[PDB]
Length: 207
Image (tube, rainbow, N blue to C red; front, side, top):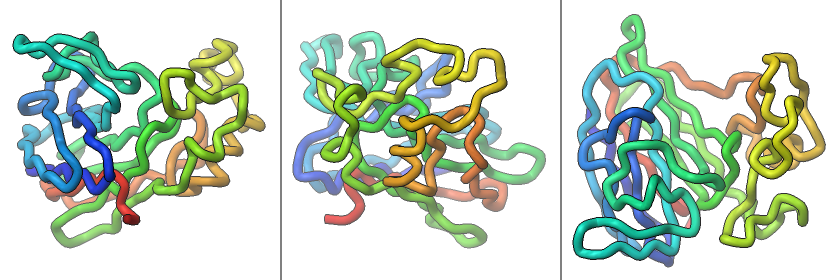
């Protein structure tokens, strides 16, 4: 499956793609304002994620750090990134269908649109100014808006017992972005697409 990653932000971002225990395609790459990077993800990929990283510095070997979404200090991500990270999430070819969503469960750093480039389903988007409107206690000094689990580490925010409800903090993310997961047990906003669909992830979609 092809995923065209486009940076419409006025600032540079370092795209990342991983399934948690391995990179997807090259795993990561710099995207200056306006640049597009197309990656290929193997059919059947389960639990894949794509996100943007901001304010990164990498040496010649591809090692360094980013203020948001850092994945073990590597340019080419092999693991998931450090919150806050707005997440484009997908599981492909799961019993004949593709499943996609956007999640704020791990916080929000950059606005995003995640849409199919093929027929059969609709896209999802979270492009509100969550960082600007972020509740004081969730603001990340390093940049972005942290999710409450990251900040407070409680069973309720992290849904560790599998029994949690919405919270004042999750409701904030849900208010700004109704179409993205605001907490673990949020009413699903996952979209079902035809198996083997192709997609486009656009950072800063409304610009």
